[PDB]
Amino acid sequence: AASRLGTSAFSDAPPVELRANWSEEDLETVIRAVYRQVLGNDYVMASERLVSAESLLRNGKITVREFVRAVAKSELYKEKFLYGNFQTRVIELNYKHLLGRAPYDESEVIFHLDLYENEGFDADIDSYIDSPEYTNSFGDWVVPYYRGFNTQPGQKTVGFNRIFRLYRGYANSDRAQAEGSMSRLARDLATNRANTVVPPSNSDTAFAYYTPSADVPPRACLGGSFGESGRVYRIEVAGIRQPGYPGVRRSSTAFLVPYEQLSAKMQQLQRTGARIISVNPA
Amino acid sequence: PSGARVFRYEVVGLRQNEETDRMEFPIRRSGSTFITVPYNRMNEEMQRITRMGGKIVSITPV
Amino acid sequence: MLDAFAKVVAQADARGEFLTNAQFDALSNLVKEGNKRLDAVNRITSNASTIVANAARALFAEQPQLIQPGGNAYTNRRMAACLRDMEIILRYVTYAILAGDSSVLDDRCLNGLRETYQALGTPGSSVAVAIQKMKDAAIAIANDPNGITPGDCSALMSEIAGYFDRAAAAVA
Amino acid sequence: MLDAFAKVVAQADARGEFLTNAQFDALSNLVKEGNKRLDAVNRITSNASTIVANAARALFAEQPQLIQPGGNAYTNRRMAACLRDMEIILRYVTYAILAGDSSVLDDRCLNGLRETYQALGTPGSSVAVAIQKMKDAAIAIANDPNGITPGDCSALMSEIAGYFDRAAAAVA
Amino acid sequence: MLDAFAKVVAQADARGEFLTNAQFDALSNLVKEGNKRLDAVNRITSNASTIVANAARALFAEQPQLIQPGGNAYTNRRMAACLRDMEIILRYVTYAILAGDSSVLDDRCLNGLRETYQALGTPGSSVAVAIQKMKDAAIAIANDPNGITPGDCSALMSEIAGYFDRAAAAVA
Amino acid sequence: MKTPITEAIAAADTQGRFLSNTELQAVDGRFKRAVASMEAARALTNNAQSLIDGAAQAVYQKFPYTTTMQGSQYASTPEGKAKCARDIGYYLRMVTYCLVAGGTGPMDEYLIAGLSEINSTFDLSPSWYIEALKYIKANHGLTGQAAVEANAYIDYAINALS
Amino acid sequence: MKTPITEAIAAADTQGRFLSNTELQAVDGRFKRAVASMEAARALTNNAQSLIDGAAQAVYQKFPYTTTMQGSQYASTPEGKAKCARDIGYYLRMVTYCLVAGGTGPMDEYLIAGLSEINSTFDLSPSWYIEALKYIKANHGLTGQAAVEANAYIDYAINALS
Amino acid sequence: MKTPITEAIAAADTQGRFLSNTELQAVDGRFKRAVASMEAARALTNNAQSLIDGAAQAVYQKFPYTTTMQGSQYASTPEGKAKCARDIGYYLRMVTYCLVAGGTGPMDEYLIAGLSEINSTFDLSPSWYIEALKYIKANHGLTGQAAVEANAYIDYAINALS
Ligand SMILES: CCC1=C(C)/C(=C/C2=NC(=C\c3[nH]c(/C=C4\NC(=O)[C@H](C)[C@H]4CC)c(C)c3CCC(=O)O)/C(CCC(=O)O)=C2C)NC1=O
Ligand SMILES: CCC1=C(C)/C(=C/C2=NC(=C\c3[nH]c(/C=C4\NC(=O)[C@H](C)[C@H]4CC)c(C)c3CCC(=O)O)/C(CCC(=O)O)=C2C)NC1=O
Ligand SMILES: CCC1=C(C)/C(=C/C2=NC(=C\c3[nH]c(/C=C4\NC(=O)[C@H](C)[C@H]4CC)c(C)c3CCC(=O)O)/C(CCC(=O)O)=C2C)NC1=O
Ligand SMILES: CCC1=C(C)/C(=C/C2=NC(=C\c3[nH]c(/C=C4\NC(=O)[C@H](C)[C@H]4CC)c(C)c3CCC(=O)O)/C(CCC(=O)O)=C2C)NC1=O
Ligand SMILES: CCC1=C(C)/C(=C/C2=NC(=C\c3[nH]c(/C=C4\NC(=O)[C@H](C)[C@H]4CC)c(C)c3CCC(=O)O)/C(CCC(=O)O)=C2C)NC1=O
Ligand SMILES: CCC1=C(C)/C(=C/C2=NC(=C\c3[nH]c(/C=C4\NC(=O)[C@H](C)[C@H]4CC)c(C)c3CCC(=O)O)/C(CCC(=O)O)=C2C)NC1=O
Ligand SMILES: CCC1=C(C)/C(=C/C2=NC(=C\c3[nH]c(/C=C4\NC(=O)[C@H](C)[C@H]4CC)c(C)c3CCC(=O)O)/C(CCC(=O)O)=C2C)NC1=O
Ligand SMILES: CCC1=C(C)/C(=C/C2=NC(=C\c3[nH]c(/C=C4\NC(=O)[C@H](C)[C@H]4CC)c(C)c3CCC(=O)O)/C(CCC(=O)O)=C2C)NC1=O
Ligand SMILES: CCC1=C(C)/C(=C/C2=NC(=C\c3[nH]c(/C=C4\NC(=O)[C@H](C)[C@H]4CC)c(C)c3CCC(=O)O)/C(CCC(=O)O)=C2C)NC1=O
Ligand SMILES: CCC1=C(C)/C(=C/C2=NC(=C\c3[nH]c(/C=C4\NC(=O)[C@H](C)[C@H]4CC)c(C)c3CCC(=O)O)/C(CCC(=O)O)=C2C)NC1=O
Ligand SMILES: CCC1=C(C)/C(=C/C2=NC(=C\c3[nH]c(/C=C4\NC(=O)[C@H](C)[C@H]4CC)c(C)c3CCC(=O)O)/C(CCC(=O)O)=C2C)NC1=O
Ligand SMILES: CCC1=C(C)/C(=C\C2=NC(=C\c3[nH]c(/C=C4\NC(=O)[C@H](C)[C@H]4CC)c(C)c3CCC(=O)O)/C(CCC(=O)O)=C2C)NC1=O
C-alpha cells in the first residue's frame, strides 16, 4: 500500500562518498537531495543557495554531515522554520528534516527544548546532527532520508502515525501546509495519544481531518452504546457542508455508531459530502 | 576566539565490523582518510573516531 | 567516470579539436562488436555467484592458513567479509567490461584499496591469488562456445584478462 | 577572530602587562581616522561587481593560456569557479579593511588556499596576478575623490594595498 | 575493549585452543580477589575531585611557568581545560582499574593524546608530571589502612601505579 | 558524464548489484542508435567551418546593435568578432562531442553549468547564442533519424540557454 | 566484546561519569557468579571430545542423506567428516568461551556475525548445527545455575541459526 | 447471542439495576433444565455422522428429481452431494449448539438470519431442508425430557424455514 499512503518511491539511499566524490554529476544530485530534505522541499531560489558550503563540499574538506549541518544552521534554514514558529513546533521540524522521524515521546521535546533555552539553537542542531541515530542511519556520506516509514531501527509504534502528520505528501513543504503556523504534534505528544493516518491528496477530494480531542467522542465506546448485537464502530468525517442550519457546526467530527446502524449512517454522511476518514472498532 | 584554528585529523584504517555492525552504511575505505575538524568540536570528534575504533595517525594544525 | 566513448571524447575535448576521422572509425568499430561485449557480460553475470563460490573454495583449499584459527579468513565474520570483497571485485570488473574502459575499475575500486588491506593486515598476495582464480573462471565462462552464435571473441577475452590483471597488480 | 583593538589587547594579554601609552595613542589614531576607513570599505563594496569583472577581463587577456582549451579555466564550470574565487578574495579583504587587521583575511580565506590550488593544478602565481589586478582597481576607486568631502588618506590606501598584497603572496 | 576474562578468551581464540587449566585457575584467582578491585575503584571515585585539585595545586607549584602570563595553562579558560583533562585521564584509568586490564585505557583515550597536545603546543612533559602527582594521590587514597576490613591490597596498588605510568609515558 | 552506458552502470552501482538485463537492454539500445549517431556527428564535423561562419553572420543580422554599440561585450572591434567566432565554434564542437558520446553528458559538464553566472557577469545575453544554435539547427543538412537526434541535442542546448 | 564488565564501562562512558555504585554492584554480582561459571567451563572442556564426537554421530543419524549425498557440502567423504569434527568443535569451543565471558560477546563476535551469509554461500543447512547443539545441550552433564547459563548460551546459538 | 442467561443480564442492564430475584429464578430454571439439555446434546453428537447420512438419504428418496435434474441447485454431481451433506451437517451442528445454549440464540445468529434471502437468491427450495429436519426429528432416538426439548428446537428451525 504505497500510493495512497504517500510513499511513492523512497526506496534507496544517495551517498556521495566515492573516489570521484564529485563524480562530476552525482554531487549535483546529492546537493539537490540535501536541499530537499533539510529545507523541507522548499523551493530555494538560485541566488540564495549556500555556495560557500558547496565549495568545501566538492573540495572534500567537509563531509555530507558537515554540509547538512551548514544548511541547518545557516540563516536560509532559520528564516523558513526556526524564526516564525512555536519552539516545540521547531523541534518537530528538526526531527523531520535532520533525523527523518517524528518525536517518539515527550522526553524528546524536554531535552531539545532545554538545550535551546540554555545553550542556544546552534547547540540544538548540533545535538540532532551528532546524535547516535544520525551517526548510524546516515554516515557523514549519506543524505538524510525519511527512515520513519521503515520500522527497522526500534521505535514506538506511534512513531509511524506521527510521521504521517508531518509528511503530508510528496509535493508538500513544511513552510506551506494545511495546519501550518501552529504546532502539529504538540497536544498529542504530551498525552501520548495516537493519531489517525490522514492520507495526502491524490487526484480526488481532500479534507484534512484535524483531530482535536477537545470535542470528539472517545476512541472507545465506553459503554454498551445502543445495546444492539455487535460492537460499536467509530466513524470519522470532515467535509459536512450541505445541512447548515446554524452552520452545521464542527464540520470535521466523529460519531460512535452501533454496528447495525452503520450502513444508514454511512449514506447520511455521504449525502453531506464528507469523505469518511476512518471506521475503527471501538 | 576559543574557536577557529581548525586542526586536520588523519585516521588509521577502521577495521569495521567490530562494535559497528549496527551502522547502516557499509564503510567503503579504511585509512588514508583526512577529516577537517574544528577546534570547538575537537573534543567530541575525538570521542567519535575512537569509539568507532581505529586510531589517529597524525594531527596537523593548518 | 568515463567509459570508452566518454574517455575518447574527454581527451579530445582537453585538446580542443573536433573528433577526427580516425577517432570516428575507432568508435564505429567499438559499436560493431558491441553485441559480443554485451553477450560476454551477460554470461559472466549469470554465473557470478557460482564463480565466486568455487573460487573461494579453491583458495581456502590451496592456502589453509587463512581458515586456520588465527588466520584472516577465520571467525566466520571475516569469512563473510572475504567473500563480499571477492564478489565486489567481480562486480566492478563486470561494470568495466560493459563500459569498455577501466575508469570504473580504478574509481570506486583499487584506489586506496591496497592501503586498506595493508592496514588491516590482510595478505594482499593471497587476494591477488583469489583474483587470478576468478580470472580463469570468468574467462572460461565468457569464452564458452556452446549455447551461442559462433564467432571469435579472443580480443574481448584478452581485455577481460587485462582488467583482472590490473586489479590483482594493484592489490599486490 | 580579532580586529585591530582586539589585536593590541591580545598581545598585551600574552605579555601580562597593562596597555602601554604607545598602544593607547595608536588606537586613538585609529579611531580619529575611522570615518576614512568606513568610506573606503563602502566604496569598494559598492563597486564590487565591476572591480571583479574588469579585473577578470584583464587577467584573461594577460595570460591567454588559462582561457585556451586545456587550461584551468576552460569548460565554463571552471570559469565560473575562477570568477567566484576572485570575488571571494575581494569579499574577505574588504572584511579585513573594515576590521583594520589581517587576522580575518588569513584565518578563513588564505588559510591553506595555496595547498588547495597546488593540488587542483590551478597555478597559484596566476591567481596572485589576478589579486593584483583587483588591487589596482580597488585602490583607484577607493581613492577616487569625485563626490566626497576631501582629505588625503594615502595611509589608508597603502593599508588596503598591503592587505591585497598579503593575500596575493599567501596564495602564490 | 577487553577486560581480564575477555583478554584471556581473545588470546585463546587467536590460537584456536580451548582455555587451558592454567588460564582457568588464573582467572579464578583474579575473581577471588575482585572485592579488592571494587573497593579501590569505589574509593578513587569518591575522592575524584580532591585528587585532581591537590594534584593541580602541586603541578602549578612545581612548574610556575604554566600559570605565568603567556604560559599554556594561563587565562583561566585553559586552566579549566587543564583541570578537565586531568579528570578525564583519571576517569579512564578508573575504567581500566575496574576492568582489570589497561586495554580500555590505551584503546580509548591516550590514542593520540600525545599527538593532540603536540599539535596544540601543550608540553607533554608537564602533563606527565601531573599524571605522576595524580598517581601518588590515587595510590594513597586506595591504600589507606583506615576505614575498612584489614587485609592486603598491595598487588592491586602496584597494578594501579602501572596504569598511571602507562598513561604518563604515552602522553609524553 | 551522463553517458547512457555509465548511467546504467551507476544505476546498478548505487544498488550494489551485478548488471541485470535492464542495464544490458539499455546499452543495447545505445549501440543500436550509435550507427545513426556517428553518421550525424560525421556530418556536422565535416562542414563545421561553413556552419560556424554562417551562424556568426546570422547573429550579426538578427541583432545589428551587437556589431555597433561600443563596449567590451560587443563585436564592434575585430577582436570581438574573433571571440564571437570562438564561442559559436565552442557550441558546435560541444554538440559534436555530445553526438559521439551518445548523451547530453558533454554538453552538461563542459557547458550549461554556471552558464547563467557567466552570461550575467560578462553581459553576454543568451539570445545571441540561442539564435546561432537555431541557425545551426536549420542548416545542418542532415536527413532521417540522424537529423532527428542532432536536432534534439541542439534543442536541448537551446532550452538550457533559455 | 559484550562482556558484562565492558558493557557497564561503556554505559558509564556514554554518560561521561565515573562508575556509580549501581555499576559496581552489577560487576560484583558478576564476580560472585564467576566461581560457578568457571567450574562449569572446566566441566564442559574436560568432556569436550566426547561431546563433539557424539554430536557428529547425532547429526549423521538425524540426517542420513547428508552422509550419502555426493557433493562438497556433505560428510559423505572423509574430508567432510573432518569438516564436521572441525565445525562442531568450534561451536562447543564458543559455548565454553561464552560461559567464561559471562555474556554472549564471544558468540556474537566469532560465530553469529555473518553466519547467515556463510550458510548460504557454502550450501550448509542451519538445521544440521541446530540438531548438533541440541545433542550438546542434552549431554553437557552440568548441574544447577551453571547448567542454566550454559543451556542459555546454547539456545542463543540455536535461535540464531533459526 | 440470545442465551437465557445473557437475556436476563441484558434485561437488567438496560435498566441499570442489580440482578433481582426474578432474574435469579429464571437462571435457576435454566440450570434445572440444563441436565436434560446436556444429555440430549451428548446423544446427538454421539450419533452425528449416522444422523447426517440418514437425513441425506431421506431427501434423496423424497426428492429423486434432485439427484438427476441438471442445475447447480441440484446434486447431480459428487460436489453437489457433498453440498447437501454439508448443509444438513450445518443444521445438526446448530441444533447441538442451541441445545447447549439452552435457547434459540445460536439458531437465530448463525442460521435463520436471512435464510429466506439466501435460499431465494440461489432459488434453492426450503422444502428440501424441511424434510431433512423431519427425518432428524424422527430418528434422533431420544426419550424423555431431552426428546421434547430437542424436537422443539428442530421444529423451531422447520417453522422458521417456512
Ligand atoms: C575560503 C573560501 C573558498 C575558496 C578560496 C575556495 C576555493 C576553491 N576553488 C575551487 C575551484 C576552482 N577555482 C578556480 C580558480 C581559478 N582558475 C583560474 O584559472 C584562476 C588562475 C583562478 C581564479 C583567479 C578553478 C578553475 C576551479 C575549478 C577546479 C575544477 O573543478 O576543476 C575549489 C574546488 C571545489 C569547488 O569548485 O567547489 C575550491 C575549494 N573555496 C572556498 O570555499
Ligand atoms: C514558546 C516557548 C515554549 C513554552 C512556553 C513551552 C512550554 C512548556 N512548558 C512545559 C512544562 C511545564 N510548564 C509548567 C508551567 C507552570 N507551572 C506552573 O505551576 C505555573 C503556573 C507555570 C509557570 C509560572 C510546568 C509545571 C511544566 C511541567 C509539566 C510536566 O512535567 O508535566 C512543557 C513540557 C515539556 C517540558 O517540561 O520540557 C512545555 C512544552 N515550551 C516551549 O517551547
Ligand atoms: C515536484 C512536485 C511539486 C510541486 C508541484 C510543488 C509545489 C509547490 N509550490 C510552492 C510554491 C508556489 N507555487 C506558486 C504557484 C502559482 N502561483 C500562481 O500565481 C500561479 C497561478 C501558480 C503557477 C501556475 C507560487 C506563487 C508559490 C510560492 C509561494 C511562496 O513561497 O510564498 C511550494 C512551497 C512554497 C515554496 O515555493 O517554498 C510548493 C511545495 N512542490 C512540489 O514538490
Ligand atoms: C456559531 C459558530 C459557527 C461557525 C464559526 C461556523 C462556521 C462555518 N462556516 C461554514 C461555511 C463557510 N464559511 C465560509 C467562510 C469564508 N469564506 C471565505 O471565502 C472567507 C475566506 C471566509 C470568511 C472571511 C465559506 C465560503 C463557507 C461555505 C463553504 C462551502 O460551501 O464549501 C461552515 C460549513 C457548513 C455551513 O456552511 O453551514 C461552518 C461550519 N459555523 C458555526 O455554526
Ligand atoms: C565497494 C568498495 C569496497 C571495497 C573495495 C572494499 C574493500 C575492503 N575490504 C575490507 C576488509 C576485509 N577484506 C577481507 C578479505 C580477505 N580475507 C582474506 O583472508 C583474503 C586474503 C581476502 C579475500 C581474498 C577481510 C577478511 C576483511 C575484514 C578484515 C577484518 O574484519 O578484520 C575493508 C576494511 C573494512 C571492512 O571490513 O569493510 C575494505 C574497505 N570495501 C568496500 O566497500
Ligand atoms: C575525552 C578524551 C579527550 C582528551 C584527552 C582531550 C584532550 C584535549 N585537551 C584540549 C585542550 C587543552 N588541554 C590543556 C591541557 C593542559 N594544559 C596544561 O597547561 C597542562 C600541561 C595540561 C593539563 C595538566 C589545555 C591548556 C587546553 C587548551 C588549549 C587551547 O585551546 O589553548 C584539547 C583541544 C580542544 C579543547 O578542548 O580546547 C583536546 C583535544 N580531549 C578529549 O576529548
Ligand atoms: C541485452 C544485452 C544483449 C545480449 C546479451 C545480446 C546477445 C546478442 N548476441 C548477438 C550476436 C552475437 N553474439 C556473439 C557472441 C559470441 N561469439 C562467440 O564466438 C563467443 C564465444 C561469444 C562472445 C564471448 C556473436 C559472434 C554474434 C554475432 C555477430 C555479432 O554480433 O558480432 C546478437 C545479435 C544477433 C542475435 O543473436 O540475435 C544479440 C542480440 N544482445 C543484447 O542486446
Ligand atoms: C557494591 C560494590 C561493593 C563494594 C565496594 C564492597 C566492599 C567489600 N569489600 C570487602 C572486602 C575487602 N576489602 C578490602 C579492602 C582493603 N583492605 C585493605 O587492607 C586495604 C587498606 C583496602 C584496599 C582498598 C580487602 C582486603 C577485603 C578482603 C576480601 C577480599 O579481598 O575479597 C568485602 C567482603 C568482606 C567485607 O564485607 O568487608 C566487601 C563486601 N562490596 C561490594 O559488593
Ligand atoms: C566551452 C564553454 C564556453 C563558453 C560558452 C564561453 C563563452 C565566453 N565568451 C566570452 C567572451 C565574449 N564572447 C563574445 C561573443 C559574441 N560577440 C558577439 O557580438 C556575439 C553576439 C557573440 C557570439 C555569438 C564577446 C564580445 C565576449 C567579450 C565580452 C567582454 O569582454 O566583455 C567569455 C568571457 C571571457 C572571454 O573573453 O573569453 C566567455 C567565458 N567560454 C567557454 O569556455
Ligand atoms: C570458528 C567458526 C566457524 C564456522 C562455524 C565455520 C563454518 C564453515 N564450514 C565450512 C565448510 C563445511 N562445513 C561442513 C559441515 C558439515 N558437513 C556436514 O555434512 C554436516 C551436516 C556438517 C557438520 C556436522 C562441511 C562438509 C564443509 C565443507 C564444505 C565445502 O568445502 O564446500 C566452511 C567453508 C570453509 C571450509 O571448507 O572449512 C566454513 C567457513 N567456519 C568457521 O571458521
Ligand atoms: C451454517 C449456515 C449455513 C447454511 C444454512 C448454508 C447453506 C448453503 N447451501 C448452499 C449451497 C448448496 N447446497 C446444496 C445442497 C443440496 N443439494 C441437494 O441435492 C439437496 C436437496 C441439498 C441439501 C439439502 C447445493 C447443491 C448447493 C449449491 C447450489 C449452487 O451453487 O447454486 C449455499 C450457497 C453457497 C454455497 O455454494 O455453499 C449456502 C449458503 N451455508 C451456511 O453457511
Ligand atoms: C554612518 C554611515 C557611514 C558613513 C556616512 C560612512 C562614510 C563617511 N565618509 C566620510 C567622509 C569622507 N570620505 C572621504 C573619502 C575620500 N575623499 C577623498 O578625496 C580621498 C580620495 C578619500 C580618502 C581615502 C574623506 C576624506 C572624508 C572626510 C574625512 C572622513 O571623515 O573620512 C564621513 C565623514 C563626514 C561624512 O559624514 O560624510 C563618513 C561618516 N561610513 C559609514 O558607516
Image (cartoon, coloured by chain):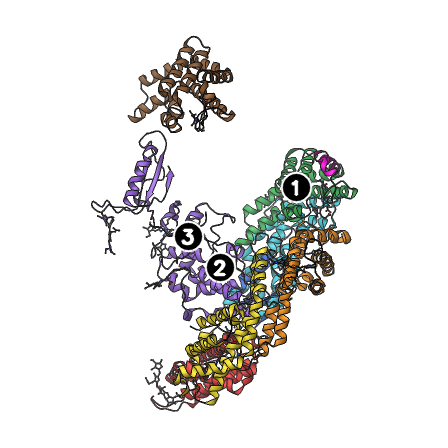
Chain colours: A purple, B blue, C orange, D red, E cyan, F yellow, G green, H brown
Q: CA distance from mark 1 to mark 3?
A: 47 Å
The answer to whether residue D110 is left or right of residue A279 is: right
Residue that carries the numbered disc 1 in the rendered image: G126
Task: Mark 1 vs mark 3: tell me if same chain.
Answer: no
Decide whether residue A242 is among the magenta residues: no
Which secondary structure, mark 2?
helix
The residue type indicated by label 3 comes to: Ile
Q: CA distance from mark 2 to mark 3?
A: 17 Å
Quadrant position of residue C32: bottom right
Observer-nearest residue: A172 or H48? H48
Residue that carries the numbered disc 3 in the rendered image: A110
The quadrant of the image that shows the C terminus of chain C is: bottom right
Which secondary structure, mark 3?
helix
Check the residue under mark 2 and report the chain it is in: A
Q: Position of residue E68 (x, y in %)?
A: 54, 72
Q: Is residue E164 visible?
A: no
The residue type indicated by label 1 comes to: Pro
Determine crowd level at label 1: few under 14, some 14-19, many 20+ residues with C-alpha closer than 10 A: some
Q: Are marks 1 and 2 in contact (CB under 8 Å)?
A: no
The residue stretch that appears in magenta: G52-67
Of badges 2 and 3, nearer the viewer stands 2
Q: CA distance from mark 1 to mark 2?
A: 41 Å
